Image 1: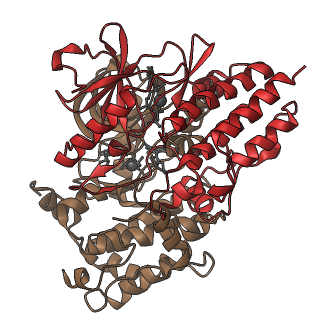
Image 2: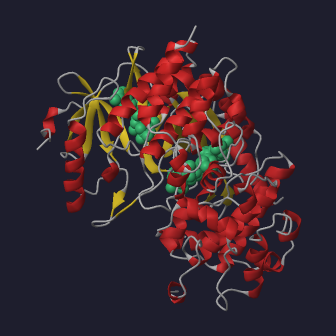
Image 3: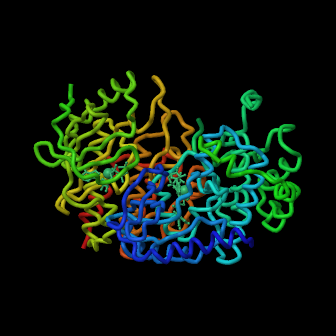
Length: 310
Length: 274
Ligand SMILES: Nc1ncnc2c1ncn2[C@@H]1O[C@H](COP(=O)(O)OP(=O)(O)NP(=O)(O)O)[C@@H](O)[C@H]1O
Ligand SMILES: Nc1ncnc2c1ncn2[C@@H]1O[C@H](COP(=O)(O)OP(=O)(O)NP(=O)(O)O)[C@@H](O)[C@H]1O
Ligand SMILES: O=C(c1ccc(F)c(F)c1Nc1ccc(I)cc1F)N1CC(O)([C@@H]2CCCCN2)C1
Ligand SMILES: [Mg+2]
Ligand SMILES: [Mg+2]
């Protein structure tokens, strides 16, 4: 890995020893970090250890047998320990709510950031894609875990310039139980997965690509920009899903994005999950070879974009 | 004017968020259910259409229908309905796993067509029939709540409201999924819902139990490619019953029966029952 990463990975492990049983009365609410369409999240202080975490709260109505399995299966996250994966402090059920406790990322999700930034630069997106590719790999090799839903609000980022994956599918029950609860308006579901076929990291890669393009232009790219709004530089959910399956994929705009980057996404967004590139290939693409070579000040760009200092 | 004064409701414990509100247990001449609507955009055209809709719902009285006790605009837009003592069908079937007797299952379905018929008789489309909206008052009687309210199950931008899929989809007829029709909500979109409810009763499961993908379900049901696996009907469910369920579940909405005939089938099935 790296010297500075091994500092950060052990610094967490040691901050995690000061954490024991997570009791709900062991917590002080600081601020709300926002809701989602499954849970709501709080920045919180763990009274015993003194740490500061994020506490995702999922209020579900499921039979206890299932709940007890979801909790069992979330304890698998004590074993995810990559610099590309958000840290995990514990998970428990109390008072009708599953709590998942994780490290605070003070930058927020890339979605929060994309709204603060309009569109995101390619030099940046480059260093993001490197991170996601690395996180998706770390989940497939060492855990045989498919993320199941790569999207900008599931990538987190912090003022030390780290880019990390979160909200990934480590308990199938929990994904399932949350989705009947609140159907959204958008969809990162690859077209095979919408038709019942599942393809290991191939269906995640598609989500990534889509997310790349959304961040790159500043708008969710289905359907594509209506010719005129492109030069500026509502849809029914059943129809987005019909479009994803029965229409060509989205593409970057010409000329304003590098040839290497328009290609990287287009290989990501192939509707056939087998022609679509895999992790081995993306990792050694032109656009990644270069963007890895580019030295970019990520933390400064982030803190500038949020309205903070350095 | 069916409004209640501001400081009339003693809003209490927060209970849960649904497809179009957050419900707090209330106090108002006895316990109530206060649902704080997600539409907190009280448009001029809206507030007069929701006022009109509360007019119709206020005068709907039936033993299998949840009492619509009126509404509130101060603080924000709210709704007061009878508080149900006792758990919802969904909690019974899928959380507590109440071991109902075969005859009682039928009678839950009978009492439900019973009520749903009254709705359609008073020309009310439910739009959102699911087992979460059927409570078992003192475990005996069936009470159907969360009916109507089309004007606040969508959000508004002027005098036009975009109808959004919200909440859970398992009960949505395929024409409601697609949203491609004029008004896709119909007496058969309600009947189709009822069909899924029957599936819950006859199988003890929600449909599409083997698909942990939501969007997959949406696409496939809308496109006609997916419908409930009916072999999962428990072994001792009346042959006459299974068939009734499949009529409601007909993909093309116009093959589905209406509640007048549905309720009839059940009572026939009830009577002739060892
Ligand atoms: N560990 C975290 N640190 C900081 N912000 C977070 C963290 N986890 C989530 N958030 C943010 O808090 C808000 C709500 O969290 P979350 O439920 O994860 O959002 P969501 O992804 O849009 N919902 P979902 O579609 O169910 O995944 C969002 O604005 C997230 O970006
Ligand atoms: N009249 C009521 N009395 C008591 N509990 C209620 C009442 N109405 C709803 N609830 C409960 O309130 C919670 C959520 O309410 P609700 O907004 O109706 O969500 P939902 O019914 O699951 N979906 P939907 O009704 O289709 O929007 C659940 O725990 C219900 O059992
Ligand atoms: O909240 C989750 C989530 C779902 C399944 C699961 F196992 C999880 F662990 C989840 N959360 C989670 C995972 C790892 C870390 I580190 C921290 C976490 F909070 N999801 C999946 C989600 O993003 C959406 C909601 C349902 C539709 C598909 N996924 C929200
Ligand atoms: Mg998330
Ligand atoms: Mg209800």
